[PDB]
Image (cartoon, rainbow, N blue to C red):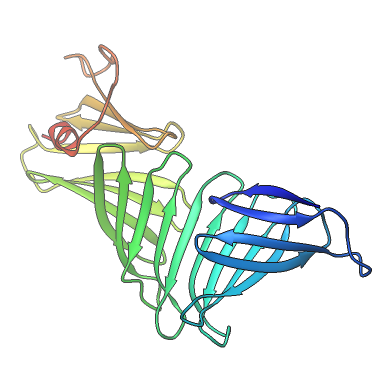
Amino acid sequence: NSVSVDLPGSMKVLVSKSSNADGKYDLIATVDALELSGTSDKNNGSGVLEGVKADASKVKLTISDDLGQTTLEVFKSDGSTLVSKKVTSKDKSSTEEKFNEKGEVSEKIITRADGTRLEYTGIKSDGSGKAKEVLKGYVLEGTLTAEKTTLVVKEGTVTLSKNISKSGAVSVELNDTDSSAATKKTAAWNSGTSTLTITVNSKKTKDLVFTSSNTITVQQYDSNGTSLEGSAVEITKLDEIKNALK
């Protein structure tokens, strides 16, 4: 009498096989221990469902028309102000937000399809906060502002910064307080190839590639400072980034 549909974000909805006299389908969904119910124009699992937690919190689940997006929202008991919101997008990334007493976002966790994460905590009304990127094998720590996320690794006199612009573009910069032209590191960012080239005393030393799989590779140049040698190695721990900056 009804069709079961699996939903992005580990949920499931039951849909009536045929519509009522208003043309609408009934929906019942299970979300952890909670039962939600609602209606829809389609028979495919899309629609809007509501329920109440044992503590009187209102819950709403919205499923996009194409079943590609789900939004799970938790509100205060009068349903007026958000407490939490989780969205799973069609690219299988996820965004989880918490809201403070006045219902402003105070935390946002973005989980990429590969499981790497951007964690923003202590978010203030100007969109500043603490930031952390969780990669495979290591974590990069830094700050958030409404202009950019800045993740930082330090080694000796060298500071490496991974900046993620507000629109999501990446740029990497290298600062070095070393004043000796023979050993001081400088670096050039090639936005086209996602590659940071480090130079010491007018010779290239290493390429750091920031890949679209959210990994970092390092490859050394020959003694000539002009040709790459060997093959790039994938960073698996923060110590290897620090070693690259020596």
